[PDB]
Length: 226
Length: 49
Ligand SMILES: *[C@@H]1O[C@H](CO)[C@@H](O)[C@H](O)[C@H]1NC(C)=O
Image 1 (tube, each protein chain N blue to C red):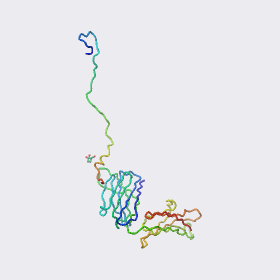
Image 2: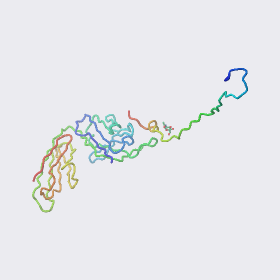
Image 3: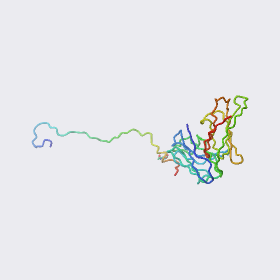
Image 4: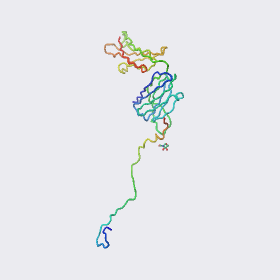
């Protein structure tokens, strides 16, 4: 139904500017308010700004005034948020939340979110983007049970973490344990995944680990072999 | 007038044409319904810029 796809986000130097977008799809972008809310990793959420059904600003927070400017475009059905003079305390997952009520004319100001999205990791630091390094982890011949053998990728050496792993085309929603990354005392991170990988008799997956990284755009299509 | 003379003979003559004439200007239109959304654009809460 509602598909609040969010675009725009990555690694930027402190003091620069960027443009965030949130293309709405599923409802009418003329009768529902959509706001912006960030969420620091494991440190709760924080409301940034918001706009009502019409072109109207409902306010900002106590730390984003003068630097952030939100704008609404009802013609293209997309909400935009401008960020100026980004600092070290602006690294969070900015979400694109909608509103449940239709915001009738004569009522009381009461906004509560109903539809949420995924968010874009907007990291602000002095480091630079690094290219990922996918490696075909060997599915060793240790065969005790049916699907005891497993193969995956060894993505590493990447500062931002908008990591999305695919196998064939963006499918095979079966058991795939994508382990979270970790800062290896150098700012970089490391990604890995584990699949079922049953008995290999030319009747298995295509052995492909597509890794998409926006700040380090590069299409890796390397295969995995035992 | 219609038989211009002053010694009109005996008979019946068609002279005028009666016509009873109006007394109001009645205009009858249907009921108002589905008013336009002018209550949420002139009595809104907040604008932007
Ligand atoms: C605005 O609201 C008031 C009170 O509800 C009402 O009297 C007025 O007619 C409304 N104005 C418009 C333009 O509808």
